Image (tube, rainbow, N blue to C red):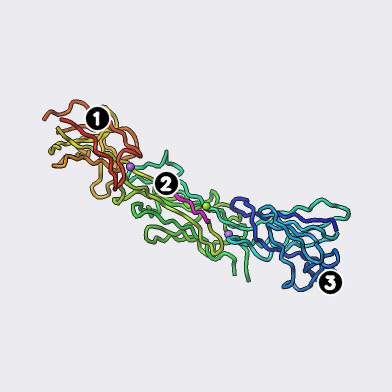
């Protein structure tokens, strides 16, 4: 009459409360024991059936007590289930249906509970359901700006299901995959040795390459754990893929370059998939009195020992070199323009190498506002002669 059960249903991804999990409540009476389920209410008491198809479905986010020959239901806190007016005795709270975009965990599906005599304190139980949170980061970058060609460290992370080794007859999880799709202007460095080799981890342990397969789609890839190795993954741990991409020749400073990741396990995924965006920088100048024949280089410091900007003709990758000979020269045509693209943000110096030859460098900033978008390019900075 006065005993009660209070359940918190949570997801494994963020310990978040989950509504719409469905439970039945059983007891065992007899020798040998016959199982019975709460079916309904009659004369201040719960009625019982041995037919599980007729068992009352208690749903998380609702509370239930005995009414006049029917259940009195009300809305409960998120992921909470309250069942009042239980008689003294031992019971099993049995999960029969997972919430949307959640999966059952085998050792969470049957929760024993005891209602004690003369005890109105709610009995507290927690029940976990597997959910997915995917994370994507660039753990080495100072900000968001990069040079074209610069190898960028990426990390994709997902919580590993608590039920990763559960079995249905026939494992519960027959695939477990991380997927990335990204801008055409990003190229995944599919490299299996050296500084930029990718790596798949269970916690801090490296998974041997034969236990997964990397495949590339159009502007994306999939990391697929081998079906036979999935039950070895750490339940509740983290699966982490660490890799490198770079901006290719298609990149320019007018767009952001995004990637997005998610998990594919047959069961659950992230409804708000993680994205990362990176940008590159640029600056435009126009030589005027528009003058052609003007040649320049870019220095990374206002000094003679500074480096020189180098732009690879094929990849458009931007690097710094120690001599003028190794530098890229920008020579103005009739339009008078100098179009410097693919730099990291920062302060740089334009140096005229070939009217009066300039006697000082022109300091310029590269940043979010220095170049523009394709529709509205920022006016080139005039260089008078
Ligand atoms: Mg999300
Ligand atoms: Na899951
Ligand atoms: Na820009």
CA separation in Å, label 2 and label 1: 33 Å
Q: Quadrant of residue 107?
A: bottom right
Which residues make up the magenta segment? Answer: 271-277
User: In the current view of this chain or complex, which residue is farthest to the left?
Assistant: 355
Give the class, few, some or many, for how many residues have Cα within 10 Å of label 3's Cα (few <14, many ≥20): few
Q: Tell me if I can see residue 211 in this picture.
A: no
Mark 2 and mark 1 in contact? Answer it, CB < 8 Å: no
Q: Which numbered disc, 2 or 1, marks the residue that appears first in the sequence?
A: 2
Residue 177 vs residue 87, the one in the foreground: 87
Q: Quadrant of residue 192?
A: bottom left
**Spot occupied by residue 9 in the image (x, y as percentages of width and height):** 67, 55
CA separation in Å, label 1 and label 3: 93 Å
Mark 1 and mark 3 in contact? Answer it, CB < 8 Å: no
Ligand 3 shows up in the quarter that is top left
Whether label 3 lies within 8 Å of ligand 2 gets the answer no
Give the class, few, some or many, for how many residues have Cα within 10 Å of label 2's Cα (few <14, many ≥20): some
**Spot occupied by residue 142 in the image (x, y as percentages of width and height):** 42, 38
CA separation in Å, label 2 and label 3: 62 Å
To which residue does mark 3 refer?
A: 32
Q: Could you say whether the residue bearing mark 2 is in a helix, strand or loop? A: strand
To which residue does mark 1 refer?
A: 362
Q: Tell me if I can see residue 33 in this picture.
A: yes
At a point 71% along the width and 63% down the height, the residue shown is 23
Assess whether residue 365 is covered by the magenta stretch. no
To which residue does mark 2 refer?
A: 153
**Spot occupied by residue 346 in the image (x, y as percentages of width and height):** 34, 34
Residue 321 vs residue 361, the one in the foreground: 361
User: In the current view of this chain or complex, which residue is farthest to the front?
Assistant: 68
Residue 350 vs residue 242, the one in the foreground: 350
Q: Could you say whether the residue bearing mark 1 is in a helix, strand or loop? A: strand
Assess whether residue 272 is covered by the magenta stretch. yes
Mark 2 or mark 1: which is in front?
1
């Amino acid at each position: 009459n006065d005993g009660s059960l209070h359940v918190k249903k949570v997801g494994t991804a963020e310990n978040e409360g989950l509504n719409g999990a469905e439970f039945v409540i059983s007891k065992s009476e007899g020798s040998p024991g016959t199982v019975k389920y709460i079916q309904g209410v009659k004369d201040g008491l719960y009625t019982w059936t041995t037919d599980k198809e007729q068992a009352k479905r208690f749903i998380t986010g609702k509370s239930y007590e005995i009414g006049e020959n029917d259940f009195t239901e009300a809305e409960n806190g998120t992921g909470e289930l309250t069942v009042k007016n239980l008689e003294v005795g031992s019971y099993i709270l049995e999960e029969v249906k997972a919430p949307n975009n959640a999966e059952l965990i085998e050792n969470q599906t049957k929760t024993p509970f005891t209602i004690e005599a003369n005890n109105q304190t709610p009995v507290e139980k927690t029940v976990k359901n597997d959910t997915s949170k995917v994370d994507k980061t660039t753990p080495s970058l100072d900000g968001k700006d990069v040079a074209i060609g610069e190898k960028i460290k990426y990390q994709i992370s997902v919580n590993i299901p608590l039920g990763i080794a559960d079995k249905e007859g026939a494992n519960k999880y027959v695939k477990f995959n991380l997927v990335d799709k990204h801008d055409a202007a990003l190229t995944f460095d599919n490299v299996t040795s050296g500084e930029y080799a990718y790596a798949l981890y269970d916690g801090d342990t490296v998974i041997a390459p034969e236990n997964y397969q990397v495949t590339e789609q159009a502007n994306g890839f999939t990391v697929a754990v081998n079906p036979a190795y999935i039950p070895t993954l750490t339940p509740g741990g983290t699966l982490k893929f660490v890799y490198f991409m770079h901006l290719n020749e298609k990149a320019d400073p007018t767009k952001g370059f995004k990637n997005e990741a998610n998990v594919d396990n047959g069961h659950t995924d992230d409804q708000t998939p993680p994205t990362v965006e990176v940008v590159t920088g640029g600056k435009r100048f126009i030589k005027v009195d528009a003058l052609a024949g003007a040649s320049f280089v870019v220095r990374d410091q206002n000094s003679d020992t500074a480096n020189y900007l180098k732009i690879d003709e094929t990849t458009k990758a931007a690097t710094w070199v120690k001599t003028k000979a190794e530098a890229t020269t920008f020579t103005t045509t009739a339009d008078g323009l100098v179009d410097i693209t693919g730099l990291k943000y920062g302060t740089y110096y334009l140096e005229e190498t070939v009217y009066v030859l300039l006697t000082n460098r022109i300091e310029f900033v590269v940043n979010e506002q220095s170049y523009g978008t394709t529709e509205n390019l920022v006016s080139p900075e005039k260089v008078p002669n």
